[PDB]
Amino acid sequence: LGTRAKESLDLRAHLKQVKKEDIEKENREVGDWRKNIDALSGMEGRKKKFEG
Amino acid sequence: LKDAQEKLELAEKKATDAEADVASLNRRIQLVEEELDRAQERLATALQKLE
């Protein structure tokens, strides 16, 4: 009975592996990009051209 | 006339100077207001994220 019960757990171990070890492929996507600021420095233009 | 001439020239130079100053300062105030508003929108984004 113990062996038969543990057989199901051993089978589910593979499913657990497929669930868990695979998500380790990458997790840095939460890392965001630069998103830099200007601090009133990137204002070096006049009212010369606006369409381009 | 010569007195009027000098008066006219000096007043014209002063007027043009004041106009240039106020125009450039208007551009500056536009830029700083843009700074303020865009920063405010960042504030709103942050508020939503934290909540």
Image (tube, coloured by chain):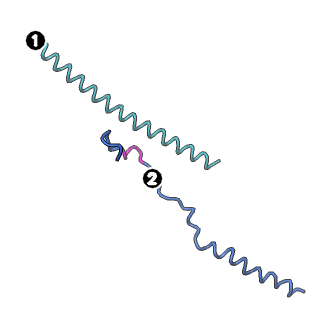
Q: Position of residue B32 (x, y in %)?
A: 41, 37
Residue that appears at 27% across and 29% down = B20
Residue that appears at 64% across and 75% down = A22
The image quarter in which residue A30 lies: bottom right
Is A7 included in the stretch rendered in magenta? no
Q: Which mark is residue B1?
A: 1
Is B14 placed left or right of A14 in the picture? left
Quarter of the image with the N terminus of chain A is bottom right
Q: Residue furthest left?
A: B2
Q: Colour of chain B?
A: cyan
Is B21 placed left or right of B11 in the picture? right
Judging from the image, mark 1 belongs to the subunit labelled B
Judging from the image, mark 2 belongs to the subunit labelled A
What residue sits right under mark 2 in the picture? A36
Q: What amino acid does circle 1 point to?
A: Leu
Q: What amino acid does circle 2 point to?
A: Asn
Task: Please give the letter of the chain rendered in blue.
Answer: A
Q: Position of residue A43 (x, y in %)?
A: 36, 44
Could you tell me how many numbered marks the image carries?
Answer: 2
